[PDB]
Amino acid sequence: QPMEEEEVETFAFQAEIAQLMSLIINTFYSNKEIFLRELISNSSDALDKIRYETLTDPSKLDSGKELHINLIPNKQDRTLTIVDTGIGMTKADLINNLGTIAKSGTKAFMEALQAGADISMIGQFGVGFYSAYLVAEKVTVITKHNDDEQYAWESSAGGSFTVRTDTGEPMGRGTKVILHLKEDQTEYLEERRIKEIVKKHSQFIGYPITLFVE
Ligand SMILES: CCc1cc(-c2n[nH]c(C(=O)O)c2-c2ccc3c(c2)OCO3)c(O)cc1O
Image (cartoon, rainbow, N blue to C red):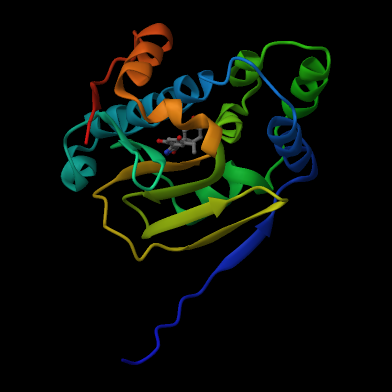
């Protein structure tokens, strides 16, 4: 019965990243499906990192040996979750990688979009994670690194994000991205569509990808 207390840290995004987010959110783009390719590619990069780091430190895998990616659509709560057993991120990694630090690609990318370039180019500018906002109104990133506790990052955009120690289900190690889909983007919860886009854009990821249906 005692009330629980939870500490939260709210951070403002870096100015151009915030501009980029408004651009992605309030502009119509037709090839939205590449958001999934970008997430799986981020997961593949993180899996590569724990993989190589373990060659020289097998203990690094005590937090989990499987190196893979799971996709979990949930039609009830309208979320598409992408989980990987990659190296994860510490709290500081989270805060720096997801918002507070300027990326040199942002401006060039925003200018390129203003010129009508395809949103698919986004990964080439180092800000592919933000493509999640093409289909999600809110994004929650839960991550666990061997050197730190499990944290949850969350943002509905609007210029800021929060970080807090995660009270949710523990992960051994890795990063889980939960996309709360916009209502007109529920196609990405359909198994056929997900298989279609993973086959089209991610046929070559070198880690198993498993789609869990129901
Ligand atoms: C939210 C972006 C994202 C990041 C990771 C991830 N986990 N650990 C790490 C790490 O570099 O240590 C990452 C990571 C960090 C930055 C990246 C990245 C993966 O891909 C492009 O930019 C991940 O595994 C999945 C993701 O979707």
